Image 1 (cartoon, helix red, strand yellow):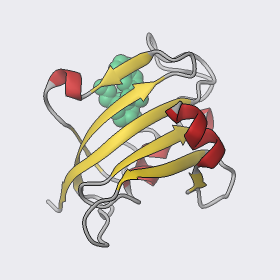
Image 2: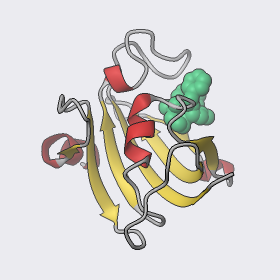
Image 3: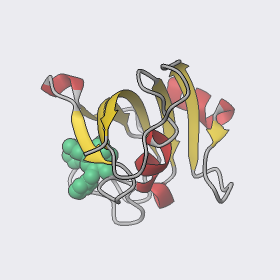
Image 4: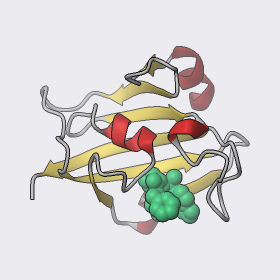
Length: 128
Ligand SMILES: COC[C@H]1CN(Cc2ccccn2)C(=O)[C@@H]2CCC[C@H]1N2S(=O)(=O)c1ccc2ncsc2c1
């Protein structure tokens, strides 16, 4: 399925080249521009654990998830991966625990040492 495919066929987008964050572009977005550090970014996403369970979805809430890019408001894999996206892009990201919740996990939904799968859609980005 999609998690296997990004694991085996994804691009390593880490600066360290440690395969900690792998990406596939699923829907090509608009032009060349990507958000910059500090932009307000608006996304839709779904996240799955390596056991196949969906742990979260913004579409199920009928509202986007909003954060300031590059400020550690989200897991490292998102600061790295959303920074690569064009407006309107949909991507798959495979996030090893060192770029996610590590050995701590996130109680209650994410276990220790969890590799996470996301589908992310970059809806918009704005400088405030
Ligand atoms: C609604 O969740 C928003 C956001 C959470 N954070 C930041 C954060 C703040 C405080 C504590 C932990 N994490 C994230 O970095 C990542 C990536 C952005 C999207 C979300 N997650 S998540 O991995 O999908 C996730 C993780 C745990 C969780 N518990 C129940 S729902 C759920 C969602």
